[PDB]
Length: 350
Length: 33
Image (tube, rainbow over all chains, first blue to last red; front, side):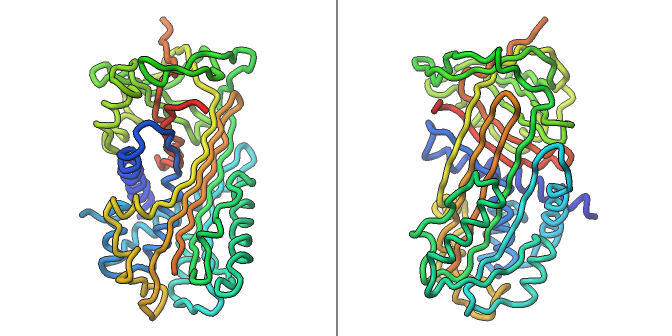
């Protein structure tokens, strides 16, 4: 039962990842994109727990909890067990995720919502003074996020995000740091050209090694995929690389046009993806980003939650709450030793 | 032979928890710096 629940949530997150990427890609075809769909889905799932009617239904459909309202209890259960799996005690690498509910001290929440939030998301409520101390409250939340992220997600919320009208902020944080199973040797790293397009390139620190990794060759679809395991292969970085640059922009036009999670799932655990000796060249790179996902989520079909018709009576008896912002901030650094990655998502309700 | 896997042009990448097959981070790198 619990195993199936975990598979359903993992599948929902995978579907959401592709949909989210596709929506982000529509407006920004030529920019770096990086996010944690785990963090975004976790924070919005904790929000969905409180949703009712069309507010809930739309969120469930966008997040792939349901197909396009009865609460998806299987999903909340799946998130619980996944969170437990990610937070397993260990000292061979770093993986942790946490959720928290920040609420206006004067605003009463339903006890049933708090016990369910604690059960399924390990989210405890912290009363804060939004009404007459929004800056105090903001810094308090940002400090917690810093602690959960080893200070890699620093000032999550700005003064434009937390105001006197703010009533709840539901936050997820995730932190990951691990060595590669097989680390690159720094002496083999050198300055090499990274080709942005057919007619453009820029210099980057290119890491190099010759070793054996699982590789899927898809000649017909013009791409290859490789898995780069972290220690004990408990997590991996997968890289999808087009065979060359075979279009007028980034080389990813075919891949991005044909991207589905069904395809991505089939590739990622394919029998054709066998252990292959490879001359691996990988850039040393780091990405940071920040976005308010309101507009994006609205364009994906999550509309009612951001309106004066929003219904969050799962957490309150009054229909006086709506989502104002969904702040997502991310960070990743890839180097010879491994990868450090981090993110936070803050659902701001007023 | 040795297969050339040279990541010197735009690519998608993601970090996965393998046992659960959960994508934790997803991205596209197409623009250095």
